[PDB]
Image 1 (cartoon, rainbow over the protein chains, first blue to last red):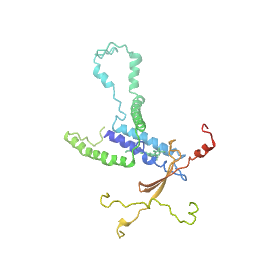
Image 2 (image 1 turned 60 degrees about the vertical axis):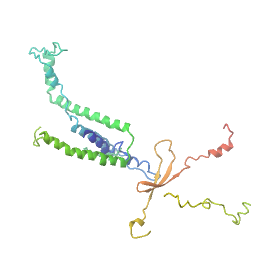
Image 3 (image 1 turned 180 degrees about the vertical axis):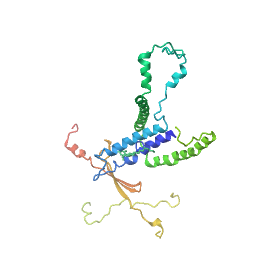
Image 4 (image 1 turned 90 degrees about the vertical axis):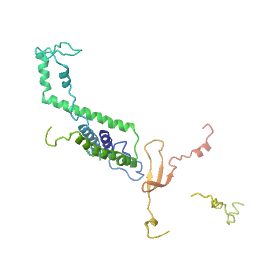
Amino acid sequence: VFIIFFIGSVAETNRAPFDLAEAESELVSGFMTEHAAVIFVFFFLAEYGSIVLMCILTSILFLGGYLLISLLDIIYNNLLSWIVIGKYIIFIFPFWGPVFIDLGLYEIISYLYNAPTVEGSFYGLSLGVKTSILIFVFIWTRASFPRIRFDQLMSFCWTVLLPILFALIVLVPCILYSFNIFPVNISLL
Amino acid sequence: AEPQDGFQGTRLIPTGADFQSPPDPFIDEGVDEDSVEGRKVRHYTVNFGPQHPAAHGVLRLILELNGEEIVRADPHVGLLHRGTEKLCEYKTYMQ
Ligand SMILES: CCCCCCCCCCCCO[C@@H]1O[C@H](CO)[C@@H](O[C@H]2O[C@H](CO)[C@@H](O)[C@H](O)[C@H]2O)[C@H](O)[C@H]1O
């Protein structure tokens, strides 16, 4: 479903390799008339902003969104020699007795982690890193393929992609019923 | 006695349509009414060129289209005819 969504999201933005319809205008202009998207930055900011927006929404739905895989869970599982003297010994094979400064670092570090500014920052750097990775994959796609003819993109949508999607529309709720996994639709989370 | 015999048109030049021969009938491989079959369809012409790449710099090909498909393609060339074959007669071989 994710791959279909990303491919659908390139075709939706009119981006290459799905841009041959709007591409053929420049080849038949002739010797008497010309285009109109000429001095306007609007349809360029409308275009680039729809690509960025299709990357953020793609990340919201299939990647974490703003979810950073938190390493603070891993350190809890590994560390077992909690010490009140600030030594913070670890029960691991590369571990030792750390000399982290309670007065200088641990008090400061703990406070900055719970700050409203810091935690918000990481939530947006996560969403930003994920949107940027997808922005790369749009640019990489334009530089990797030739163009598809309009009839061929139409066949891709209507005789390949949508049949698979409607097949998955049947199957997915059928499995969610079979494993008692229908979520509650009340305001939780 | 051309061009003298051609002044009065006493001779006609044997065109290829004179020497046309019917196909052999045996081994030969492959109307108006109220129906819409007799109806005709209009075509529209399209001026293609010049494309961005350098090689197809001066192409003005005029296509006749039935919908999407090409009915007849008429390239108009000469947009880069510079008279090379004539200028070569006024130069030495090395020139
Ligand atoms: C399914 C959920 C979707 C959620 C996100 C929805 C975002 C919708 C934003 C729409 C904004 C306008 O949408 C966008 O408009 C611009 C300008 O018309 C189009 O861009 C167009 O003009 C530019 C030149 O200026 C061309 O390079 C481009 O090939 C052409 O298609 C984009 O093809 C279209 O995607």
